[PDB]
Length: 257
Ligand SMILES: CN(Cc1ccccc1)C(=S)S
Ligand SMILES: [Zn+2]
Image (tube, rainbow, N blue to C red):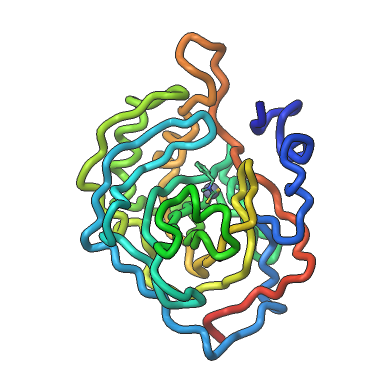
């Protein structure tokens, strides 16, 4: 099965998922000097006040904090988006070292991790149908750098002991994802894909310019997770990121000058 190891990592994925070499794959490098400011891009609207988190799951390649997406409770709208996109889950990608871990890069700079807040277009009725559509998903990507702690992340860090291994889940209610957002909503946007198999080309990427800072202790706790199941040989869940893919026939747009 696919993974992030030597024999099943990103360079292998195309054998089971040929779209890996497609025309709108993610992540990409964001060349800040060639991104074009688009004055017609609307401000992003992030409406998370009624978000209802349900649980947290180690799925063998990341941990997902899952939300009730059966009503319009936590939605993303505006920006490059037409219509309303509902929050279904968030997860992170991170490194074995503070010098790598993000999937998008900024002028080739790698951050220590990257948060993906995953939303699906309500016109398609559920996530599974949405991923089959070119405008099915909107993923808000936020870079993490190591420095000061992010207090709003700590409840996530502290439950990771309970989901160390693949397939473990824990109740995780009343978590407020507003505590993971930077001050500014300035962003870059482009059409791309999921960054894990099945690599479907269904994502409008909205990548925030401003990173959040997390502490070294916080990211160290991410690195104690396991890719394996309980009772299987221990392999630390680190470097669960795909490298940058060719931009091909795409232009990254900026919401800011
Ligand atoms: C939705 N995904 C794929 C994914 C699903 C679960 C955990 C990690 C990644 C994107 S990378 S935004
Ligand atoms: Zn992701």
